[PDB]
Image (tube, helix red, strand yellow):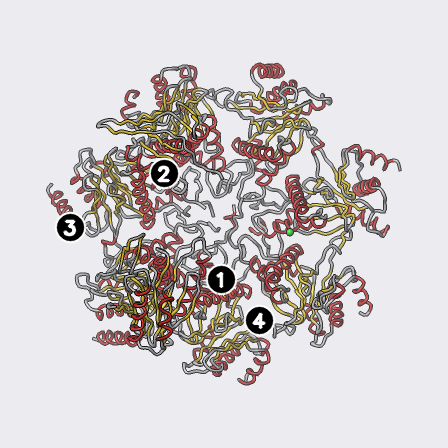
Amino acid sequence: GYDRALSIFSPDGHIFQVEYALEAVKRGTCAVGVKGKNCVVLGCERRSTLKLQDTRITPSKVSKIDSHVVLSFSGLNADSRILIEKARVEAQSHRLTLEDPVTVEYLTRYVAGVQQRYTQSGGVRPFGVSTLIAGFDPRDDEPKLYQTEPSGIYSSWSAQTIGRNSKTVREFLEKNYDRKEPPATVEECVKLTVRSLLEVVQTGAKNIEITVVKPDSDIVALSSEEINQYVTQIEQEKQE
Amino acid sequence: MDIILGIRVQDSVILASSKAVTRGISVLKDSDDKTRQLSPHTLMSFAGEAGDTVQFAEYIQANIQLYSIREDYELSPQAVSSFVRQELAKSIRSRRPYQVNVLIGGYDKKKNKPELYQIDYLGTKVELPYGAHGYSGFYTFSLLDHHYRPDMTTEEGLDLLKLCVQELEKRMPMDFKGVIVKIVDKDGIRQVDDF
Amino acid sequence: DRGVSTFSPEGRLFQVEYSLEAIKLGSTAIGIATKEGVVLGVEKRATSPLLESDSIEKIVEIDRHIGCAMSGLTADARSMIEHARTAAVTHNLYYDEDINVESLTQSVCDLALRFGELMSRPFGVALLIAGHDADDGYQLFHAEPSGTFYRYNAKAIGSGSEGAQAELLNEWHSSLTLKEAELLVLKILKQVMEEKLDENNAQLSCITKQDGFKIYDNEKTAELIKELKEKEAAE
Amino acid sequence: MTDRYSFSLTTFSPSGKLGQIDYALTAVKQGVTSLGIKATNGVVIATEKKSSSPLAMSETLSKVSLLTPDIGAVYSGMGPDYRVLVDKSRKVAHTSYKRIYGEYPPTKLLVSEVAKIMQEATQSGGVRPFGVSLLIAGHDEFNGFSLYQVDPSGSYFPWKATAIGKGSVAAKTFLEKRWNDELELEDAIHIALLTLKESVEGEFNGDTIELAIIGDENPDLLGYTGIPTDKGPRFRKLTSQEINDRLEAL
Amino acid sequence: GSRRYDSRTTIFSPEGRLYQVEYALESISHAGTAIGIMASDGIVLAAERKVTSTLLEQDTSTEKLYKLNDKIAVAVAGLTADAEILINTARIHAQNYLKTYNEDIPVEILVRRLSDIKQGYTQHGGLRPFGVSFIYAGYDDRYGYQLYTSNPSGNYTGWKAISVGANTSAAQTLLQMDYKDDMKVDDAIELALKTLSKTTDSSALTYDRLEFATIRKGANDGEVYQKIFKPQEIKDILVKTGIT
Amino acid sequence: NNYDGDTVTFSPTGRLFQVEYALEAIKQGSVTVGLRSNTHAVLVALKRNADELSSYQKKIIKCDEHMGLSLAGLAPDARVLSNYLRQQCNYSSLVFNRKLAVERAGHLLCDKAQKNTQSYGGRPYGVGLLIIGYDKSGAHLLEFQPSGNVTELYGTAIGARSQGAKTYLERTLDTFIKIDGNPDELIKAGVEAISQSLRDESLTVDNLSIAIVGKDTPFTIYDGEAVAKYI
Amino acid sequence: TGYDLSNSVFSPDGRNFQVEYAVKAVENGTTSIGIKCNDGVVFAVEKLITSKLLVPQKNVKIQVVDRHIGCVYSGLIPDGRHLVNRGREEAASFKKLYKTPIPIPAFADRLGQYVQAHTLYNSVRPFGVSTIFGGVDKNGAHLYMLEPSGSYWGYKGAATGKGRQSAKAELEKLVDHHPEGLSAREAVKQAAKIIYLAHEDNKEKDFELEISWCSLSETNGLHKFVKGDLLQEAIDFAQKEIN
Amino acid sequence: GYDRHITIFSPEGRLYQVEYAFKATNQTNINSLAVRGKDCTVVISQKKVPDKLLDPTTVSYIFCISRTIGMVVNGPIPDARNAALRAKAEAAEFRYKYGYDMPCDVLAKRMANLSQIYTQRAYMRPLGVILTFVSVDEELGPSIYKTDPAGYYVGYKATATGPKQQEITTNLENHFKKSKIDHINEESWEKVVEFAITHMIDALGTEFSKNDLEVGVATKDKFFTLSAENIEERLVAIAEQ
Amino acid sequence: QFNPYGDNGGTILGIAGEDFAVLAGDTRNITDYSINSRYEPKVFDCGDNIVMSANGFAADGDALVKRFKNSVKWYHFDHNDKKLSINSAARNIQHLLYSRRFFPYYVYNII
Ligand SMILES: [Cl-]
């Protein structure tokens, strides 16, 4: 078998393949995660270079791993499918062997472990993908939001963004998000998520996707018109 | 577990399954539920050798739940039954086969039709209006042959099912400790808590 | 290119030496061993204020009598911790007893040089393994990706290591109490950290014979930080 | 030991070229000319027996090879590569077809199998592409007569008539003027001999030319009688004498 | 040892791109243009054969359009030999799904499977990727008529109208201009041919330089028919639409 | 230069540079001395610490009741090779009810190290070993180099500044070989030998490591206050 | 250029430079010889005394294969040991299947094919030893010499190592002055002389002589080391000739 | 320029490692010749023992592959013996599996196929040898088939291999241009050997003693090599006319 | 049919005192009605102040004792010459025995 060590240390103590994988993430479309008091919202950018697209059948950016956990990403699309598939398999494997669904933290820990394994295994390159994993633990009403990256490190976030121009939207979130008082309702949480994407997106038409996840496996994706109403209200307040 | 019945009426499928579990000469449990929900509109009851039954059922359940998540779509009862059959037909020529007989009751939301599939441990599949495994059919099929119509209501199906259970309780040597009855229709799966 | 297990003209493995450079970039971790217990402390170093700092887990329990702190590519430590925990519990299964701290450390280090063309590269993380057993008492080990481990009375690893190690050189003596050690870790962490030390960006932990391995609450550490400030202002 | 070349030796260059395939095609270009013409009632394939030494017995070296009773092949490029491909092509015709369906594969599917083998040497680890282009002529009940070309990349195309190797460009032009959809087999053989004379320098006779046909069934070449449905092979290699007879009416 | 000669086909550039995937796409841009257009009552697949000869046997030839099953077909752009490897795998996956579930495979599931295979060649194994881009035209009872594309990266996307191969930039602009949602098959046939006629590098567009196919519910009652056009039928539709 | 990228490559003058670089790792290692008489065999090792808070790296490893070695170079490689010896000593006992001869133990180490010098992918061992033992032919001392070369000696030393101790033993050859039935005097001679390789630092209680094996003496290691007698 | 960086690569000459570099390691080694006598063979080798601390007669270089074959080599000593270990496996499997002890020509090819195999791939390094070996079989005495390339021939006399030219000259004289042949006891004496004469190329350090022999009359066709009085007698004869 | 180190195509469509293996073929500086009689096939080759210390009986480049098949090699001895051992194994296996003695031309093809694989697979190098197989085949009669590092093989009326192959080749060509037959019209093999030696002498322009030559002869049902004294008898007959 | 098991007889006895322990066993080894040996030791000193006897099938008994003695040796190597406590030896022996759960050591063991 092909055993070649592709991910290796350099004289200055860097693993370039892992760092170049982060550059692939930088290229990917922007993704954002914001957790309110009783919900988490996942926002995603859709680049409008591709029209004549069939939006019914085109792979959506936010993926359900289980009925209570979702995963969005930035980076190589093909790579993300492999992580999503493994995560979905592990989710059912956990339910089967332990008789409880996975915690969001556990699922994140697994996906992060897969990413890490691909940084010190022979013959393989790292995943050019960073993920945002969100949801609610079984019989728990505390929101959960985690991030992973090609190196395999993971951590929990009150709010976070990844992908292209993520530096700008993180700047926005850092000044707009208050920890002592997070978005109390779904409306406030979605509004703050749309606002953050409007710093980067371009047109607020079919370029913004929003997915709201509430406790007890209550997950819904907003439509174009619903999002368009947020886009309208934000700019009308801005004209002042 | 020995006893599992099934009947497909106008607008639903009804599965009745015994409650007894016996180890040696002692009845350990008289409230056992010999069924697994594979999807919101598909229920599978099972009977066979100890252990293999639950292990197989849960294994199938996991696979169908995985498919549902991957495609964001519920497989038709027919598609699920074919998957289950293949797993058993695969199993029979294994080193140690899984000794499990199943009934799959589902409501096809596309065709708006209830469907009942009977599959034994060899992988022998048949679609039926009513079915059973083991010796259950020997006692009950004569009643079902006589009373069954395809335009029966769910309430009529339950009454015919009560008559079947009464006959079993009269002529079977084994005490199976009654049955747990479940109904599968357009609204999903629910349990009849008084039977 | 060149082999992964290649020797340099000086007689060192290139990859092992390069991994040590990655460890120098990691956040600071300090360990101090006393006769009353061993203290472990780390710099959390959150990359953003939105990152919930309590999810940063750089101090980890291996067994009830063994703890562990990490510095460097912290993702690489997960499989090392998994192996450590397995080894510790497996030995308890085979021998109905606690495993020696040295024996645990040796088992972890045996993974280190299992790389070639096994894993494709050495680990990019160093570990401070602290514990207690009946034979050799309170112990602190430094486990490198070279497969070498030294025992220490006190040790610092990460970016502020040589500055901290010089400080630990002067401060450590064989009669240190646990309370004195706690403050000493906090003092030196505060000295080498970029941001101002508080209960949210730094974490303490210890291992004692009685209570075993314990990670300190943010409320408990906060009091020890306040106690430190006052005793430094006292002269 | 162990084969430690588990990686591809053929890769895309910045311009999108697969270097090793191009170079393999260059090796084919240097090779001796061979051609194929399809008639209404048959197919002909031909090439020059370029003898390396006059002490060598060129009859022992067969450039035109029977693959099945109704399928024949010829090449241009590296001879050894061709020889092993014929061995594999003969075997695959049995393993992946005859032992399953109880009959010989149709021309297009055998070609497909040969093509597959050549594609895999273009992608698999630690191997170079085959340095040959094949012309495969054949007949089967439902597709009739056919002629295919197979390149080092694994790509294959059906032809009415074509040529490969040294003087292919000039030969293909010559065939375009002479070919029509009403040619009888003898007419195609005549055109094959005319076309092949242009690319040959030295001696031009039955001993320096190798020529075969896919035509009528040959019950005389079957080897047994008693089964009406078995009527014999359609592949037949022309003798040295049979070639010379047609060179007088040239 | 052997390391010396390893090209390392599955690595990132400093910019975070996959070298071999990018170069494979460069190869595909020289291949004959293939176009897919999805309408309300069917799908059209049109494709241009590369500089042919008069001596090529066209009626028994197939380089562009391939049948995966009765409901799904693909248009190819790139190395034909590479495509046939993948096509046979796809045909098998469809039959596996049919044997398992006793239902025809949903279009997206087949597409995802082939795209995952392509992905694998970019992340592990040290082998070159497949120099192929597909247009998938298919039908199932969930989403109805569907168009997809996949490329050597293993990434796939859905479309109303799409082109692959040569001059996709020019072709995509022309399709984006004249395409409408309420369009029908007969109109889509005309759009596909007109687009090829303008983007072609050849002097003129003729029947012998084209492969054509439709997937219609224009089959007697609720069912789907695949039509791989014959040379004479392509000649007739060229006259009908007024190109020759 | 161009021929030092891997172990599978000879240089134009017939040298193996990766092996020579592994040999260099031994020279960087701390000094250790080996010497024997006709009744006993002794190892003396100068242990090295990282700093004042650190412990002193152990240098001597026991392989069997009658055999053991001291190391100089990569310590993990010594662990691998000593583990192999432990197994081989043990295979000889379990299967043949036979204590493994010291000479045969050397032959096994030689052949294990050699395989790593002729194959692609692997690397040579980066450690030197001094094996002492007492078997059916009396006391023995061996020197192992990761090139594969194993040598039986009366006395020797390896590591940094080992040349000083080696010269001393070469002078003392006729004296220490005759020290039969006196373990303490043989250790003294070893401690005096290793002292010829010291600079700036001297032999302290947690610095010095000694091991001995003999006629009626199992392989035992002395550390801590057990060696204060010899300081 | 670059043809000498990888084993099994043909240069434009048609040469395998890696094998030729292995020869340089052999030429760097100590001198070893072989002499074919009337009813057997004699092997001898130069052992450089690097230090007084080397235990005399302990670091044995000549190795036995089976019970009738002797092997000696110059160059990388570990490589030679590896080759003898293989030789012993080859001789064991031959005797296992065919009952009779392996014939010398048969044994020679077993080594030859193995060494040649290490010139076929870049994943292995050629052997850094030339091996002189031989013994007595059913057809009589045989002496062979095997190079890094896998090349071997039968010999009347053989020599390799740093003092090979000097030795070869001495062997050539014996072949000329004894066409009828040489006795086993004579060959031992001559072997000693030749090693002493060949020691002029390694004259810096003093050395230790080591001899072995297989003879039909003297050792019953079995390989034995020359020891005690017979060794001293050969040393005396050698010392007398240099003075 | 790694296309010259392993067996992959150069831009010219060439395999340089194969071409360089052909050059290794002449490293021994030995010339061989093969001819066919009525009932026999003869092969002769130069023998050079430069060292006096060598045992001349063990110096050979002719091999007895099977009882019917003989093989002479042009190239270094290690590769020669490698090829010899393999051919012997292949010939024995063939007899076991298919119940009859492996023909000369079939063995040639088999070895040629093995050689072809080395030109295509990267990890294996070509053998730097040219293998000339000789027999009296039970179906085809006297047979000469030759294999090279490219994997090429063909039958021969006669052939020659080595540094001076062209001189020997032309000499043989000219003889067969006169006689107008594909063989040496002679009853006994002894005279066919005498022809072979005579025409090598004429072509090379050198005289031979008994120790300068090596001879192999194939007859029906056996191949055998000649001793020095058998060759001497051959040389005496040549000189006496 | 080959029977891999046999019965060598013998009887063993272990008694624990307040600050001492004894492990006794007869020295007779037998098959069927024959005496193999009148003095074949059955109770062994295994080191670290532990004694063992595996009674029943002598070949499996000798094999087990041999493996535990080996286990004590490697316990010293792996854990810095630490003394193997009696409770730790007992648990170790459990795992030695259960390795052959499906081809058991046909012995009744005491330490
Ligand atoms: Cl073959």
| Residue farthest toward the right in the current orientation of the protein | H241
Nearest the viewer among D43 and I1 is I1
Nearest the viewer among B128 and F220 is B128
For the residues labelled 1 and 2, the Cα–Cα distance comes to 61 Å
Label 4 near label 1: C-beta < 8 Å? no
Of tags 1 and 2, the one toward the viewer is 2
Residues at marks 4 and 3 on the same chain: no
Mark 3, residue position = C219
The spot of residue C222 in percent (x, y) is: 15, 49
Q: Residues within 10 Å of mark 2 (few under 14, many from 20)?
A: some
Kind of residue sitting beneath label 3: Glu
Of tags 4 and 2, the one toward the viewer is 2
Kind of residue sitting beneath label 1: Tyr
Residues at marks 2 and 3 on the same chain: no
Report in which chain the residue with disc 1 lies. E
Residue E62 is tagged as 4
The spot of residue H147 in percent (x, y) is: 69, 48
Mark 2, residue position = I97
Q: Secondary structure at mark 4?
A: loop
| Residue farthest toward the left in the current orientation of the protein | C234
Nearest the viewer among D151 and D14 is D151
Residue E23 is tagged as 1
Residue C161: quarter of image: top left
Label 3 near label 1: C-beta < 8 Å? no
